Image: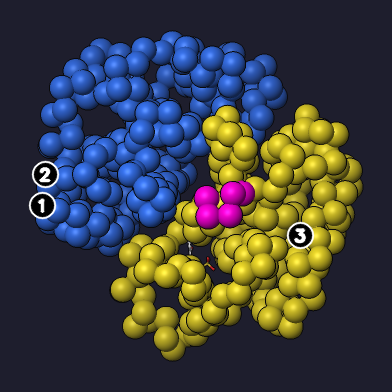
Chain colours: A yellow, B blue
Amino acid sequence: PPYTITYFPVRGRCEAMRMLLADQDQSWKEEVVTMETWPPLKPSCLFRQLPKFQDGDLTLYQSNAILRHLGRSFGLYGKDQKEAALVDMVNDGVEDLRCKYATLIYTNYEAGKEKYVKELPEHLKPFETLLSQNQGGQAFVVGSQISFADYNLLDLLRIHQVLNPSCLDAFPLLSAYVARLSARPKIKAFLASPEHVNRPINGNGKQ
Amino acid sequence: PPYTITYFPVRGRCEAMRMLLADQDQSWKEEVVTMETWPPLKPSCLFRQLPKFQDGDLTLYQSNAILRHLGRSFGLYGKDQKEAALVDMVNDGVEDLRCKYATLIYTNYEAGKEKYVKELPEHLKPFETLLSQNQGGQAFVVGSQISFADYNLLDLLRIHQVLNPSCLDAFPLLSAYVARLSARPKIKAFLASPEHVNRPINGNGKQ
Ligand SMILES: N[C@@H](CCC(=O)N[C@@H](CS(=O)(=O)O)C(=O)NCC(=O)O)C(=O)O
Ligand SMILES: N[C@@H](CCC(=O)N[C@@H](CS(=O)(=O)O)C(=O)NCC(=O)O)C(=O)O
């Protein structure tokens, strides 16, 4: 610690790590980058993009690398080696779908939305399946304790319910899971926050 | 162990993990899937895609989760928690470019090649820089020993020299890096093996 997140004024790729830190009782500083401060900041960013994260003397880029680091710092990475590998698997499945939603939103929202929405159940089904194989869907996506991939999947499922309000109809454990995890008191508090409610999900007005 | 890779007849998302295993003196079984056997196997794959990897009784999917699993299993994840964060970030930068190379190859090869090749220096310069900062570029991408991220970046660099043979000309540290790590005796023995040589880089004939 201390922690500082530098990012655009959107939820985007940082709302999962914000919920993690909130649920872990951490406080962090928000360095908001606007349209005017982005073109000069940009060339000093290693992969020329945001997020950027500072944790004491460590500066990190790449949102999943920031989640894996916080996962190691708070013991949110499985109870053993097999479990760590399964948490990585789920998080990459989350990242693949997060990538397709970003392409839809930012590049083909109007024409592609219905297509996207029609293929979506095949992309959500693997998570319903993991949840049924694990402790009756009553616990987390891997194991009996929360991992960084649960914050990232919770975020993904919540932005997709905005995109398509009935997308979890065929998936009961996924609907119960969104409800359960959203009611965790520090996450519930964060989701009610002005900071959370006042920023768009994405940076182009589409949602 | 034992290790079985199930995948299509290509280098694709499996050559980095094949090189890692060879360099580590491991043997593995190759289960090759074809156009005829893929449509029945596809519904049993968790995220409906290959590679699938078996390590004794652990079945994994997601190419980077498999590489992180092997990094954990073989001490190829940096010397401490800060280095592990850095290895994760490097590997995620490789995956972003790997996913753009796959879009060019599979959706836009002929029309996109020139624009892709023009933007490539900007996507390679992050790696050159990383190397500049690490023992003057004479070691690996993070620290003093190899990580799973070096296997993945080396594969990414080698398939980009096939795409555009002069791409590393402005990047002397990356150039030297490819030469150095490809000369590692077990990787060089792998790279000359018919098993490697006869496998196409991609599944559609483009390179
Ligand atoms: N792989 C990167 C992707 C980050 C990325 O795409 N960043 C975007 C912002 S956002 O889509 O995540 O909101 C960016 O900085 N874009 C500005 C630019 O490319 O100039 C990560 O996961 O951190
Ligand atoms: N995130 C997955 C991506 C795997 C993926 O794209 N798999 C392709 C094969 S390849 O492009 O990597 O060669 C596939 O299974 N395609 C068949 C299908 O989607 O039906 C990973 O990293 O492993």
Q: Do the residues under discs 2 and 1 have CB atoms within 8 angstroms?
A: yes
* Residue matched to label 1: B172
Where does the magenta region start and end?
A: A72-76
Judging from the image, mark 1 belongs to the subunit labelled B
Judging from the image, mark 2 belongs to the subunit labelled B
**Mark number displayed over residue A158:** 3
Give the Cα distance between marks 2 and 3. Answer: 46 Å
Residue positioned most to the bottom: A36
Q: Quadrant of the C terminus of chain A?
A: bottom right
Q: Is residue A172 visible in the rendered structure shown here?
A: yes
Residue visible at 31% across and 74% down? Answer: A43
In the image shown, does B7 or A19 lie closer to the viewer? A19
Q: Secondary structure at mark 3?
A: helix
Residue A133 location (% of width, % of height)? 78, 29
Q: Is residue A50 visible in the rendered structure shown here?
A: no
Residue visible at 36% across and 79% down? Answer: A41
Vertical relation: B30 (above or below) A116: above
Asked if marks 3 and 1 fall on the same chain, the answer is: no
* Residue matched to label 2: B176
User: Quadrant of residue B160 in the image?
Assistant: top left
Within 10 Å of the Cα at label 1, are there few (<14), some (14-19), or many (20+) other Cα atoms?
A: few
Q: Amino acid at mark 3?
A: Arg
Residue A77 location (% of width, % of height)? 58, 44
Q: Secondary structure at mark 1?
A: helix
Within 10 Å of the Cα at label 2, are there few (<14), some (14-19), or many (20+) other Cα atoms?
A: some
Give the Cα distance between marks 2 and 1. Answer: 6 Å
Vertical relation: B103 (above or below) B159: below
Q: Amino acid at mark 2?
A: Ala
Q: Amino acid at mark 1?
A: Pro
